[PDB]
Image (spheres, coloured by chain):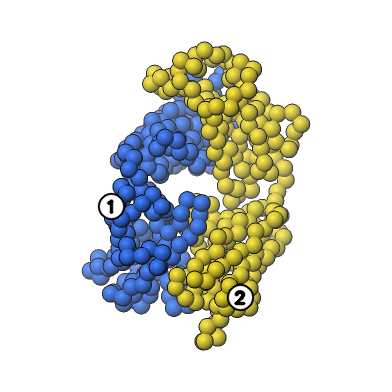
């Protein structure tokens, strides 16, 4: 069936700039009625896909006039004019000229904003978790930009890698930052063998890591 | 207002049939459209599954072989997906949508429903409060949280103060290990408001019919 390819955006876009996103079909999507059967969708973080453009260049009802589609029968462009923070998400094309109405794999738009250092907080295990024999130590690294960040755990001054799980949010639709959580899980018995628990965040906004600790 | 909404089990065992319902409001499934099922896999690839039109005429993606049936019940304004003999590869978020001849869906996609295909057991989360170690720089802000540990399947929903606290919240994607998920949620409030005023996270896990409230109390 028809192969749809999308280009990645290599660079983040500052609010107010415009950006073009492209997709390509292995087969022409121009139909015998003279219409070209290509749709564009935006999937904002955590939401269902929203149709922006159908028939290659027709805007869906309610869609901002900042979104416009153009192209030939095989190469298509979505232009986003004067990008706003809320435009962040993944843009998909879909061919609608023959079954199985294939989608491209998406193009993620990232918004460029001013560098922001993470707000770091660390939390000891709760009494409740300790009663069940477990001990998770949690560190939040909130509202930073750009997305690249490193978290290191130290117990009694020794770097600890085992038992660490990390999770990252998508870019925020309002302030264009990212956040991350890191959780170190140990048994209660192992937790109680040590005193000092530390999470260290290294980010481009500083030469020295932001360090947060507590003592059991 | 044309709306569509999916419902059905969030967990199905391998080899059994997955069934989902799409309930259409503000529009008759007798108006002339391709009432469509689409799914989005982990990692976000989208796949068109098929449609029903004119009550009884269907078409399906060949990728699904002979495993898919779409039907409808005009009396209930509902159409249905049945996908037989599922495997873990069928784990996805399932959407229903209304397509017209020209590919226009309007705003008419459902919110989506997660279905996990797994032999693992439904398990409700343990919810633990995350309260600051000692004190720090007040007259500014304080970050609290809750740790939602050891549930299956996805999803959970987290709110703070029953949804009254919506600003300054970060709920992180879950991480899976040993057939159990864990996620955390942080909330940041002015330090003048806590501990003076209470902060509670509310955690719902529909798949196990459990909802837990955890008040965050100072250590």
Q: Which chain is yellow?
A: A
Count of numbered badges drawn on the protein: 2
Is residue B191 visible in this depiction of the protein? Answer: no
- Residue B7 higher or lower than A202, as above or below: below
Residue B183 left/right relative to B17:
right
Residue A118's spot in the image, x, y percent? 65, 35
The span from disc 1 to disc 2 (Cα, nearest Å) is 41 Å
Which color is chain B depicted in?
Answer: blue
Crowd rating for badge 1 (residues with CA inside 10 Å; few <14, some 14–19, many 20+): few
Crowd rating for badge 2 (residues with CA inside 10 Å; few <14, some 14–19, many 20+): some
Residue A2 left/right relative to B64:
right
What residue do we see at 60% from left, 37% from top? A142
The circle on residue B16 is 1
Quadrant for the N terminus of chain B in the image: bottom left
Which quadrant of the structure image shows residue A64?
A: bottom right
**Residues at marks 1 and 2 on the same chain:** no
- Residue A173 higher or lower than B197, as above or below: below
| Residue extending farthest bottom | A33
Q: Chain of mark 1?
A: B
Is residue A9 visible in this depiction of the protein? Answer: yes
Nearer to us of marks 1 and 2 is 1
The circle on residue A89 is none
Q: Chain of mark 2?
A: A
What residue do we see at 31% from left, 75% from top? B57
Query: Circle 1 — which element?
Result: loop
Residue A40's spot in the image, x, y percent? 55, 67
What residue do we see at 27% from left, 68% from top? B72
Residue A170's spot in the image, x, y percent? 57, 47
Query: Circle 2 — which element?
Result: loop
Residue at mark 2: A74
């Amino acid at each position: 069936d028809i192969v749809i390819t999308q280009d990645e955006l290599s660079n983040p876009v500052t609010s107010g700039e415009s950006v073009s996103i492209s997709c390509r079909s292995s087969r022409s999507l121009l139909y015998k009625d003279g219409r070209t059967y290509l749709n564009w969708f935006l999937q904002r973080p955590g939401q269902s896909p929203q149709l922006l453009i159908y028939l290659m260049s027709t805007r869906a009802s309610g869609v901002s006039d900042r979104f416009s589609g153009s192209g030939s029968g095989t190469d298509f462009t979505l232009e986003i004019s004067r990008v706003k923070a809320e435009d962040v998400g993944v843009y998909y094309c879909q061919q609608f000229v023959e079954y199985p109405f294939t989608f491209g794999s998406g193009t993620k738009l990232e918004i460029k904003r001013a560098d922001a250092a993470p707000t770091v907080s660390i939390f000891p295990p709760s009494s409740e978790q300790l009663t069940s024999g477990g001990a998770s130590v949690v560190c939040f690294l909130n509202n930073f930009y750009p997305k690249d960040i490193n978290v290191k755990w130290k117990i009694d001054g020794s770097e600890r890698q085992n038992g660490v799980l990390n999770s990252w949010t998508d870019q925020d639709s309002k302030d264009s930052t990212y956040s991350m959580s890191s959780t170190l899980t140990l048994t209660k018995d192992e937790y109680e063998r040590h005193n000092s628990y530390t999470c260290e965040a290294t980010h481009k906004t500083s030469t020295s890591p932001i360090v947060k600790s507590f003592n059991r | 207002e044309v709306k569509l909404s999916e419902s059905g089990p969030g967990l199905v065992k391998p080899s059994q049939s997955l069934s989902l319902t799409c309930t259409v409001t503000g529009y008759s499934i007798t108006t002339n459209y391709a009432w469509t099922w689409i799914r989005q896999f982990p990692g976000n690839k989208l796949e068109w599954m098929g449609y029903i039109r004119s009550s009884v005429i269907t078409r399906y993606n060949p990728s699904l072989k002979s495993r898919i049936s779409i039907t409808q019940d005009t009396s209930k304004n509902q159409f249905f997906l049945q996908l037989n003999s599922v495997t873990t590869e069928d784990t996805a978020t399932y959407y229903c949508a209304r397509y017209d001849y020209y590919g226009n869906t309007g705003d008419y996609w459902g919110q989506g429903t997660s279905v996990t295909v797994s032999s693992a057991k439904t398990t409700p989360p343990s919810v633990y409060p995350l309260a600051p170690g000692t004190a720090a720089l007040k007259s500014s802000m304080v970050t609290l949280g809750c740790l939602v540990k050891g549930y299956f399947p996805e999803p959970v929903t987290v709110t703070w103060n029953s949804g009254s606290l919506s600003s300054g919240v970060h709920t992180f994607p879950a991480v899976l290990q040993s057939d159990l998920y864990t996620l955390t949620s942080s909330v940041t409030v002015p330090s003048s408001t806590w501990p003076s005023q209470t902060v509670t996270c509310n955690v719902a896990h529909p798949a196990s019919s459990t909802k837990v409230d955890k008040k965050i109390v100072p250590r």
